[PDB]
Length: 143
Length: 150
Length: 144
Length: 144
Image 1 (cartoon, each protein chain N blue to C red):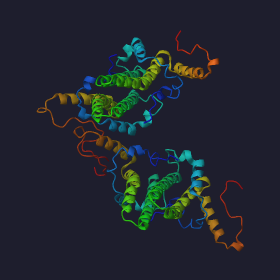
Image 2: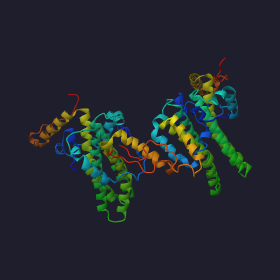
Image 3: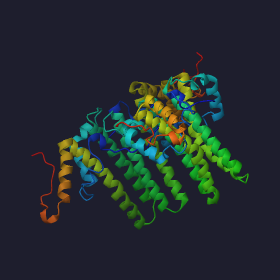
Image 4: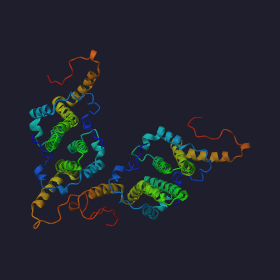
């Protein structure tokens, strides 16, 4: 299968490739936000929305990945090799998981249309040469 | 965050806590079943159903765990340690993925009410001692148990 | 041109590979079945279905392949590479031909919907563990 | 069997023997024509026409034959007879497939009636001795 996890939400992996990898917050920050804002709705027995249905699975996937990596590191011998596997998991898997978490949290919070427009505008920005690039990077806001 | 991936679908891990590991097809078998029965909808741009959404997410999670574990193994030269990590993954995360994929495929196929009734009855069965339960488990199928089509 | 010989019938190579390759009857058996059941319709100057229009072309393709393989084998000096070429043709192309002939004969005989349901059901069956499936395999039948 | 792949479409292998074997375009040219004109219908999931149902199978036959001949030539350790292999192919199977693709692309572009009338008229022409044969041979066209 060639599943794109954003195609049903109107985006694509080429649209989120606009944003760099240094843009997405830490997974701890994203999960703290998710808790604070939608704990009672993610722990709820209800299809409140596809964004919830997907954020739950993303949280569980992060849990499984962290469990595996922790077990590996503990059963591992060299601290260099431990930090090495940590770097690999962080970059690859953390990047993808926080792409997903960011997308879905931001959608729930602001709007799917707003998030797509934000990706487009951020692409405009990050493509603009720095001599004509405003320092006020785009940012999602409700106020 | 105390999330149950089935509570949203009317199930629980305590309801699937009975189904043994022997009950779930291999992950390759389940992914083939998906690719062959619902690919045109899993690769679709539509929210066909919560089951499709969860199935997409589960497939992504499995692919990611496979990348991780494969890289780990190929970097751990010792085949003993490689097979050890493989046992761990196939026992915990592979089992959870089989459980989830089975739940969702079986729901899409037969019905949520039907699958939950089947889980209740299978629990009644597997909780019962063998000396007092029928030997042939309860069966969920798209066919008469004679297995003939017309 | 990225053509699927089944998507005009509602199936797919991914769905017919969903079954094992040890399941499909031999090509001799399938051609005999055809000559027995639909010869006077395949040799007819009528379409009568898309299934016949496809089955005729499948049979002719098999004829051409057999002709070529036989000719190369006959003109090949050694008797050890004929086994290699016949194994290659059998597996690779004969498998596709078996799938196609089975699909079309079974469709004409039982029903397109029944054949597709049989595909999915037999796949799930052969993929399920034995202790939690019906014990005897599924089969297509016209006899109530 | 005695399947004639054209009598389902109103012709015969002896009504196309009116045209020589030099008359038929190359398979490359014919597949290019098909891609140009009926790609989105050959790739379609619809029984758009028996001509489509047959063109798809012809293209797949060509694919399988090419695969086989390529594999054979590769494993073969002499061009001296690799060329003879491909000669046999282009002489028998390539020719049959050229006839088939020509017939179907034409019956799709111009019409079955027009194509059969063209075959009859071209038989008249190519039978007429050269001393009495007009130079403006018949030809299939949408324009004068």
